[PDB]
Image (cartoon, rainbow, N blue to C red):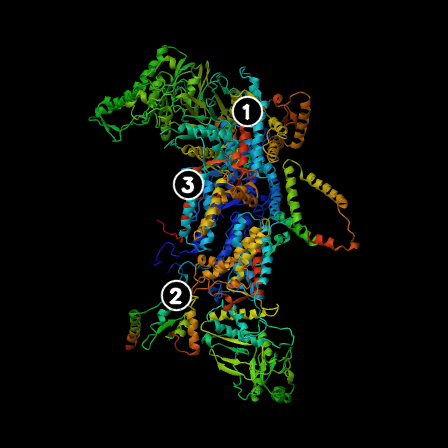
């Protein structure tokens, strides 16, 4: 009856739209299921411009590839929102949504109405949240031990690159925090670390720096590259005027005023430079090994470069907006706009400042600080995609170690949490039901659908997932009567079980909590949508 | 998001195949598709019904109000409409009467079914509702019958049968059209009363000849068949009377030719000189035996050579050409002759009798008069139909066939079994089925009560086409049926019916004086076909079409 | 027109109709063209 | 000639009435599955690509382009129900679509003139409002426990019924915060702020009184946590103001050009001194802020926020109590925001968020909704607006009417008794409304999987016993009364649904012709 | 169900004209009056004649209502009724076909 | 590697071909899903020539309507041949083939090889034949019972 | 049997996207594709190596045996070749010697 409204309008009702939601989610899952696990496949994104991007994360894949199917758009927007807050779980949510639909679609053909199916999802999900509190283990972060942070950070890097580069990047992402902590304030910000993209050495030769690194080099040759003692002066004012707000001009009566009107603009430039030179010599005069460095956010007049060249002052222009807040944390100084107010107290301190020339550009390196409140990570690569592949591995590793400090509870990984929910959701007894036979249908579909995560890991390794999970159920049966608590994981090497706590594999709290809740809403709305309609004016 | 999945895995069938099911309001669209062609036949119902013009692809125009004839030239698309189209064609062939009733009744059963489906009644329960109500409907038709035809032929009694049937088709003048058809029926009846023989009648015996020009009042009834023919040798008024002896030959008149390689063989000039005079003596010897028997007319079924037509003009023998077959077959039934293929002398017992053969101008061309007289009665009489327009001549020919088909209804059953006309048949069934719906417990009473509501279309159609308000006239008619039956017998209130124009307010007293009645044998098959036509549409949950 | 095509005779737009004084003027001038040819 | 260039051919008579009724029925047929607690969902595709998945009646109609001219009038009926009330937009089209479906076998069959039917529809509309008024009972509007069960009426259909226990606490404090004494509470949706934050959990939410801004601080030294915040709203930008007269300065002496830049720096410092007179802790402006005015406010500890939405400034003035003043010379201690507290900037990777907590009766609140995805979060936003709209009509009038099939059938029973007593030409169109009110309770059974034949047959027999509280269950389909389960809806929702359907039915029945090609 | 198009079934084949409304029977009246317009000046001994040229370029001059309607090919259903009465009147009596 | 053998060719293998047999047989079974049973739906076939075929037999649906999918062609020839010899079982075989593909498709996604799945079909089918001997009921034709032929014909 | 099912995934992603995966191709197939450009560098290696003429769309002709210079002016649709092209670019930028050995 839709064509009577519009001739070009189309629709698919009841099972016509139901087959779309099950197939489109299964087709999208089949592509992204091969990326789950350390043995997962590597996708190469090639656009019309010829750019090559190698990443195993579903956030970049779904962003570069436009999805025509409307059903998979909900999964892409759900996996995108999962990467925003938790920085992880893109592939996990995609694999859960498609599995919740296929398991529930089998009961629909048996005569089960989708309404009671959605009831079994919400009741079983609330019981999983209660089990999540008992299954998680609280940790003490006051000791700041390295061994605990290395194993958690390595687990996220094993899903990106091989084990050779993982061992190199593991202490880097572990050192990504270090001196940044607060006991009372609880505020933790990962935007203070800088991601540098440059081609130098090899991707495995990168190292961590304890201080800020800038991409701007010395504008004048006489500016000393290496400075033992430097006082960073933050200047947000532009020394070179781009334009005057009020329109004005210079009208000279005689040619003698031409050089005078040109010197009139020299007074305002020298007025800002007069207080800067007096600030350097204010501390101590004729003092070797002590330099003075200015980092400016706006442009610097090339004419004024010779003013600082005689005093051996390093100047940097066109700094990033996020760089101003980082100068206070690293150098310990204070952000200043104009030069009207200066003092040695607001100046920063650095133990080593040097610059290196890579290609046609020069980069500024600042390190050796007393109590630096921020740091940076230098990402080097041998090609174009090496900068994008390592960056996606670090950014996904930053959010992993952040949840450890934000939440002291750590949940073991390697599919140990999904297997534990299988036996718990089989029989709920009289605890939570709400109906006779109506609710138990949706709970059974949600319980067997959580086993796709451990089975997908085995399929990427080339083994039999049914044989791996067979020995898992046999161990959990004997562990209950032996009065011993054991966490059974999945090992992809020999095709046997393992212990995630001993093997060093753990998962974040916010990633697993938002994955179950996020995938439940996506799969529920698709089961509750019986019609797919398209209408509008072209 | 930009483009739909466009029904994935639809490649199982060709792109021209479409699936339509009772769900998604398509069963309502099928009922709504009936109303498009239903209103076309509503204005054509009754004596005030309006004829329709339908132009085919060849340019032929047939103007008729008959639902069975109109649906022939129309191209039908929707599949369930073809169920309604083919249902009206069967009623025209079988009983030759009640074609517009099957079209209207089967269409109203689907209209009242739209409310039945909306209330949640399954297709199975709706079918059982009409089947149980139809069996009770056929039983009440035999209880409400009044009067009988009794004797086969009567001057007055034939005005209560053919006349009310032809009143709806080209109403015009009443007694003019009724006398022309009723006269031709009395000629084809074998009569022979008290003999105990089984009566017989043929619907193809009476033939209608369409002749343009003149007026309807100038039409007459001819006991013989009328064709357009030009006599070859000469024309004869045959005033010498003493009737005639006529013979019919289905084979042409000519020298018998070998079916394989007919060839003239002449060895010498002696055989060539006698070859020209030899063929002349063959036809002379064959035609002499026919002329000696007193045969003044010979009917030929194919082309006759010129050498054979020469000796036929010598003895003054007429020549008739009867092409094809059926035209020649009905000629022998008039004179009672038996054709024989040979050219020899016919048997005197197989010769026919025709008193006069005349050739006069009627519509501008020469027609031959086979008309019979009082004695030596003949069968398969023809009716000369004069009209100004050829379009009126086509439907009146079918209007006469409706009266001829009504005569067939006087043979197979025990009698005529006249029913009250003017829509009084379908109105009385409303009060009887309403009481029948209450006597049946359960949920099946919903389809039974609505089955009687579909009978309200007959009084509403006759009132709407008459230029009267259906809201004022129809409830005033139930006042006669709302008083049920009194404490005394002899209740004449069953004769109340719907009146056209005039003073309105019901009227025409009892229809017994009006003499318009209906046939019981027609209403039996009219309800059965119309019910199965609507049942078939409701019994189809899914419809599949090809190429469109 | 009321919105429906009105065609009395096939090839409606092909055939033309002349009436009134213009129909008589075209007939006289048609003979004058033939006359001036024959008069020479 | 062509005469009229617009639809020279005309379709009139019964052909135009069928096209208007058939197209109007198709509008209600698609949303039949959208009614009831078991109702399904509908997905829509706009030419922009944004996907909208909801069971709401209005959201489906306005996003579908209908080529049928008379069927577009059915699309705007939900806008009347949404703008005036916001609840019951689905029942309006189902009722209005059933009227024309039931009124169809009259002009074609009974040949009754439309105006004759219109006179019967207006008389049936007056009697319908009396039946709804009789079945309505007053309740306490100050009872918090009673208003929680009333908001669950529209929630039972929506997917948020799982969070309904939490959702009622969010919508209750939202309406109570913005309302004030004066036409009674005169609450307006514009004062309620609903912010959509991707990610998080739906079970964890709180009602925040204030304005949630996504803008970061203009300077790193700016304190993100203030114990006693003071908000001063300024519409004038802190950047140097330029005259619109296009003043051109002719510079002659050498000290003229250097003085212009100094005066520009003196006025920016002067405008900061006018602000520091009251010593505000916070500064919020709707325009850009120059880098020179940032340093002058560092000594006074003035946190500056730039590029704030224009409508958000009016919402800040309600919570903080500050008065908006454009010029810095008129700033006084009375115009400074007071009683505000709990100013903190929470660190989230996506955006920087600022929190405000209040301690002239008009207030405002910002509800932070955390969903599982951006598209589901758009659904909770729409479900929260419809949940707060139910509490509006409860506070306007104490009248409360039953729902769930009890109100629709209570009218049809009263219309059946008066129909037999009319005995006239208007008796037939008067019975059309009685059968038109049956679509809503019949739809609830078809979506629940029950048998509408046996349930509706015994349902009418119950209303004849003298009780109007008998409804239809959405799950089991029981004939049990609605007093036990507690379904109740404001009378305004029932009145606006019946009034709109009657006024819309009379509009399409009066259209005897459809023409196009005008191109005005 | 076999496709997302789901075409709407039309009762009549494409190309069929419409009817009912208002003025459908009036269209048949104006068709006969327009044909009458040509035969009116041909009535009476002082009447005029009509020149008709067919597609074969066959010149024919006739004031007779029967002959004029034979030259032109009338595709209008209702206007052909005037052709039947003109040929029927000419067949029997032969005169009065114009009247 | 087929693009090197032929300039223009179309092929689908492994997971692409696994969805061919499962999905195509699912759409064919759904057409005959409402057909099976005495209360089943009634379908009418109307071709471009104007003919009308109204029946509940699944064989007429397969022969009159063309099938582009090659998977259903194997099922259509199997369902047609079942009605040839036994006069019954057209819609039964379609429901057996289409469903057995889907019931075994869930384990194919689990990593189970198709051969060991089909090997279990023969083992389970041979048990249906041994059970068929004890399941069937013997009837003696020497009694000439007319009521027995009435109930069987009404099926 | 005339038309293929077209697969359900055809509606997923777009028709312009092409997929090469394990068992779907590549796997020493695409390795045989770069042998055309690999043989190009084999003839240019050594003191007896052969120079190659390359005409850019702009018309400038660069004749050299350097693999880093040749692969820079050539427009190559095959993506995995760019992995080898960008590998030779680093050899020229940093060390500046041995570009033919890397390829």
Label 1, label 3: how far apart the Cα atoms are:
44 Å
Up/down of A425 relative to B205, above or below: above
Up/down of A92 relative to B366, above or below: above
- Binning the other alpha carbons within 10 Å of mark 3 as few (below 14), some (14 to 19) or many (20 upward) gives some
SS for tag 2? Answer: helix
Question: Which residue is tagged 3?
Answer: D79
SS for tag 1? Answer: helix
Question: Which residue is tagged 1?
Answer: A509
The answer to whether any part of residue G103 appears in the image is no
Image spot of residue G8 (x, y percent): 56, 42
Question: Which residue is tagged 2?
Answer: E29
Image spot of residue A378 (x, y percent): 49, 23
Label 1, label 2: how far apart the Cα atoms are:
87 Å
Mark 3–mark 2 contact, CB under 8 Å? no
Image spot of residue B132 (x, y percent): 60, 55
- Binning the other alpha carbons within 10 Å of mark 2 as few (below 14), some (14 to 19) or many (20 upward) gives few
Label 3, label 2: how far apart the Cα atoms are:
49 Å
SS for tag 3? Answer: helix
Q: Do discs 3 and 2 share a chain?
A: no
Left or right side of B157 for D275: left
Left or right side of D179 for A252: left
Which chain does tag 2 point to? E
């Amino acid at each position: 009856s839709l064509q009577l409204l519009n001739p070009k309008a189309e629709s698919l009702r009841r099972d016509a739209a139901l087959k779309v939601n099950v197939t489109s989610a299964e087709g999208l899952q089949s592509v992204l299921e091969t990326n789950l696990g350390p043995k997962g496949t590597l996708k190469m994104l090639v656009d019309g411009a010829g750019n090559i991007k190698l990443t195993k994360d579903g956030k970049v894949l779904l962003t570069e590839m436009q999805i025509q199917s409307p059903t998979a758009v909900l999964i892409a927007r759900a996996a995108a929102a999962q990467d925003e807050i938790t920085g992880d779980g893109t592939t996990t949510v995609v694999c859960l949504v498609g599995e919740l639909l296929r398991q529930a679609h089998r009961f629909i053909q048996e005569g089960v109405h989708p309404r009671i199916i959605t009831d079994g999802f919400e009741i079983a999900r609330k019981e999983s949240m209660k089990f999540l509190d008992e299954f998680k283990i609280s940790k003490t972060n006051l000791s700041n031990d390295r061994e605990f942070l290395l194993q958690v950070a390595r687990s996220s890097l094993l899903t990106k690159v091989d084990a050779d580069l993982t061992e190199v990047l593991t202490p880097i992402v572990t050192d990504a925090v270090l001196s940044v902590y607060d006991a009372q304030a609880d505020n933790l910000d990962l935007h203070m670390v800088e991601i540098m993209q440059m081609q130098h050495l090899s991707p495995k030769d990168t190292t961590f720096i304890k201080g800020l690194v800038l991409d701007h080099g010395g504008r004048h040759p006489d500016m000393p590259t290496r400075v033992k003692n430097a006082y960073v002066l933050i200047l947000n004012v532009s020394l070179e005027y781009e334009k005057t707000e009020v329109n004005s001009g210079f009208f000279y009566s005689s040619a003698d005023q031409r050089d005078k009107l040109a010197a009139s603009e020299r007074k305002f430039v020298d007025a800002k430079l007069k207080k800067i030179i007096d600030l350097k010599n204010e501390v101590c005069g004729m003092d070797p090994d002590k330099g003075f460095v200015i980092i400016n956010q706006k442009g610097i007049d090339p004419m004024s470069l010779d003013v600082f060249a005689k005093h051996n002052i390093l100047a940097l222009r066109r700094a990033k907006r996020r760089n101003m807040e980082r100068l206070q944390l690293v150098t310990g100084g204070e952000a200043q706009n104009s030069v009207e107010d200066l003092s040695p107290q607001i100046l920063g301190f650095s133990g080593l400042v040097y610059q290196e020339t890579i290609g046609e550009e020069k980069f500024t390196y600042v390190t050796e600080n007393t109590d630096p409140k921020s740091c940076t990570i230098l990402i080097k690569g041998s090609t174009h995609y090496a900068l994008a592949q390592t960056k996606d591995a670090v950014r996904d590793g930053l959010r992993a170690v952040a949840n450890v400090l934000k939440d002291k509870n750590i949940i073991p990984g390697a599919g140990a949490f999904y297997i534990a929910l299988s036996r718990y959701l089989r029989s709920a007894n009289m605890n939570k039901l709400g109906a006779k036979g109506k609710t138990k249908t949706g709970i059974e579909a949600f319980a067997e659908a959580l086993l796709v995560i451990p089975k997908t890991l085995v399929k990427n390794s080339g083994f039999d997932p049914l044989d791996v999970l067979a020995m898992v159920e046999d161990e959990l049966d004997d562990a209950q009567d032996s009065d011993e608590t054991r966490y059974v994981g999945v090992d992809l090497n020999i095709g046997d079980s393992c212990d995630p706590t001993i093997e060093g594999i753990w998962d974040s709290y916010r990633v697993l909590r938002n994955a179950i809740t996020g995938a439940t809403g996506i799969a529920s709305n698709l089961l509750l949508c019986d019609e797919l309609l398209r209408a509008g004016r072209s | 998001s930009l483009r739909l999945p466009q029904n994935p895995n639809a490649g199982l069938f060709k792109q021209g195949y479409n699936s339509y099911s009772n769900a998604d309001g398509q069963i309502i669209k099928s009922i709504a598709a009936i109303r498009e062609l239903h209103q076309m036949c509503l204005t054509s119902m009754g004596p005030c019904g309006r004829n329709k013009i339908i132009v085919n692809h060849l340019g032929k125009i047939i103007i008729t109000n008959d639902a069975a004839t109109m649906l022939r030239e129309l191209d039908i698309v929707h599949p369930a409409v073809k169920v309604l189209v083919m249902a009206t064609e069967q009623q025209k062939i079988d009983m030759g009467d009640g074609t517009n009733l099957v079209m209207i009744l089967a269409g109203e059963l689907l209209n009242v079914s739209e409310k039945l489906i909306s209330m949640g009644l399954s297709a199975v329960e709706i079918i059982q509702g009409y089947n149980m109500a139809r069996k009770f409907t056929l039983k009440e038709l035999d209880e409400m019958v009044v009067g009988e035809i009794t004797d086969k032929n009567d001057k007055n009694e034939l005005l209560k049968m053919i006349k009310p049937v032809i009143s709806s088709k080209k109403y015009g003048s009443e007694d003019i059209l009724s006398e022309l058809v009723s006269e031709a029926v009395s000629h084809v009846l074998p009569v022979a009363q008290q003999a105990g023989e089984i009566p017989y009648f043929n619907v193809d015996s009476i033939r209608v000849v369409k002749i343009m020009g003149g007026s309807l009042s100038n039409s007459t009834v001819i006991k013989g068949m009328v064709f357009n023919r030009e006599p070859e040798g000469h024309v004869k008024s045959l005033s010498e009377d003493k009737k005639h002896k006529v013979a019919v030959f289905t084979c042409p008149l000519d020298i018998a030719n070998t079916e394989t390689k007919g060839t003239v063989l002449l060895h010498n000039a002696q055989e060539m000189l006698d070859f020209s005079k030899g063929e002349e003596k063959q036809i002379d010897a064959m035609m002499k035996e026919i002329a000696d028997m007193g045969v003044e007319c010979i009917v030929a079924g194919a082309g006759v050579g010129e050498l054979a037509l020469h000796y036929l003009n010598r003895y003054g023998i007429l020549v008739l050409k009867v092409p094809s077959k059926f035209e020649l077959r009905r000629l022998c039934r008039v004179c009672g002759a038996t054709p024989l293929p040979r050219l020899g002398a016919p048997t005197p017992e197989e010769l026919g009798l025709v008193e006069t053969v005349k050739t006069m101008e009627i519509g501008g061309d020469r027609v031959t008069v086979f008309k019979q007289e009082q004695g030596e009665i003949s069968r398969t009489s023809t009716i000369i139909l004069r009209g100004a327009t050829q379009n009126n001549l086509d439907d009146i020919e079918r209007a006469i066939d409706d009266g001829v088909a009504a005569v067939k209804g006087l043979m197979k059953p025990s009698g005529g079994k006249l029913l009250p006309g003017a829509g009084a048949t379908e109105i009385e069934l409303i009060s009887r089925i309403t009481k029948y719906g209450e006597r049946t417990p359960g949920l099946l009473q919903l389809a039974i009560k609505q089955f009687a509501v579909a009978f309200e279309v007959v009084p509403r159609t006759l009132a709407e086409t008459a230029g009267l308000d259906v809201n004022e006239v129809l409830p005033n008619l139930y006042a006669a049926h709302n008083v049920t039956e009194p404490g005394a017998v002899k209740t004449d209130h069953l004769y109340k019916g719907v009146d056209i124009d005039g003073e309105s307010d019901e009227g025409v007293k009892d229809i017994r004086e009006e003499n318009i009645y209906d046939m019981l044998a027609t209403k039996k098959f009219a309800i059965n076909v119309a019910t199965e036509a609507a049942t078939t549409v409701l019994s189809i949950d899914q419809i599949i079409m090809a190429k469109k | 027109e009321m919105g429906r095509p009105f065609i009395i005779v096939k090839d409606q737009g092909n055939k033309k109709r002349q009436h009134g004084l213009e129909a008589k003027k075209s007939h006289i001038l048609a003979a004058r063209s033939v006359a001036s040819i024959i008069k020479t | 000639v062509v005469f009229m260039n617009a639809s020279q051919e005309r379709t009139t008579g019964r052909q135009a009435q069928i096209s208007n009724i058939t197209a109007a029925k198709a509008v209600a047929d698609v949303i039949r599955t959208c009614l009831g607690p078991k109702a399904m969902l509908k997905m829509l595709l706009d030419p922009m690509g944004g996907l909208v998945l909801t069971n709401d009646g209005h959201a489906i109609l306005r996003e579908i382009d209908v080529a049928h001219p008379a069927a577009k009038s059915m699309l705007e009926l939900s806008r009347t129900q949404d703008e005036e009330v916001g609840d019951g937009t689905t029942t309006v089209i189902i009722l209005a679509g059933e009227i024309l479906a039931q009124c169809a076998p009259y002009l074609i069959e009974k040949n009754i003139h439309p105006v004759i039917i219109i006179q019967a529809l207006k008389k049936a509309l007056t009697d319908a409002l009396e039946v709804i008024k009789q079945v309505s009972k007053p309740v306490d509007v100050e009872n918090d426990a009673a208003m929680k069960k009333l908001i669950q009426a529209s929630i039972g259909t929506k997917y948020v019924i799982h969070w309904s226990e939490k959702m009622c606490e969010l919508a209750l404090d939202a309406v109570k915060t913005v309302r004030k004494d004066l036409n009674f509470e005169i609450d307006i949706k514009r004062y309620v702020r609903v912010e959509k934050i991707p990610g998080g959990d739906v079970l964890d939410s709180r009602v925040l009184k204030g304005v949630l801004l996504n803008k970061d601080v203009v300077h790193p030294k700016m304190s993100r946590h203030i114990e006693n915040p003071r908000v001063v709203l300024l519409d004038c930008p802190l950047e140097y103001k330029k005259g619109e007269s296009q003043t051109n300065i002719e510079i002659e002496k050498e000290e003229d050009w250097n003085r212009i830049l100094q005066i520009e720096e003196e006025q920016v410092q002067l405008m900061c001194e006018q602000i520091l007179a009251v010593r505000p802790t916070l500064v919020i402006t709707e325009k850009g802020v120059s880098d020179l005015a940032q340093h002058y406010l560092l000594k006074g500890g003035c946190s500056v926020l730039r590029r704030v939405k224009k409508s958000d400034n009016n919402r800040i003035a309600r919570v903080t109590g500050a008065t908006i003043v454009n010029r810095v010379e008129d700033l006084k201690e009375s115009d400074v925001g007071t009683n505000c507290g709990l100013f903190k900037v929470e660190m989230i990777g996506d955006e920087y968020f600022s929190f405000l907590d209040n301690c002239g009766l008009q207030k405002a609140c910002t509800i932070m909704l955390r969903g599982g995805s951006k598209d589901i979060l758009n659904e909770i936003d729409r479900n929260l607006q419809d949940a707060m709209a139910v509490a509006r009509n409860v506070m306007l009038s104490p009248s409360l009417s039953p729902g769930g099939g009890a109100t629709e059938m209570a009218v049809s029973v009263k219309l059946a008794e008066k129909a037999k007593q009319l005995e006239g030409i208007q008796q037939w169109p008067y019975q059309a409304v009685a059968d038109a009110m049956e679509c809503i309770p019949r739809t609830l059974i078809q979506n629940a999987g029950g048998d509408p034949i046996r349930l509706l047959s015994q349902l009418r027999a119950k209303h004849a016993q003298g009780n109007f509280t008998t409804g239809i269950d959405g799950d089991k389909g029981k004939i049990v009364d609605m007093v036990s389960y507690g379904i109740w809806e404001p009378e305004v929702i029932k009145q606006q649904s019946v009034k709109t359907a009657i006024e819309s039915a009379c509009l399409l029945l009066r259209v005897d012709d459809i023409v196009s090609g005008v191109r005005k | 169900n076999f496709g997302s198009q789901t075409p709407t079934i039309v009762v009549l084949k494409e190309g069929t004209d419409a009817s009912q409304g208002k003025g459908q029977i009036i269209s048949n009246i104006n068709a006969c009056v327009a044909v009458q317009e040509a035969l009116k000046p041909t009535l009476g001994p002082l009447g005029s004649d009509i020149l008709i040229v067919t597609s074969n370029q066959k010149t024919t001059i006739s004031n007779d209502g029967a002959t004029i309607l034979k030259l032109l090919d009338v595709v209008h259903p209702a206007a052909k009724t005037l052709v039947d009465i003109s040929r029927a009147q000419d067949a029997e009596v032969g005169d009065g076909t114009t009247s």
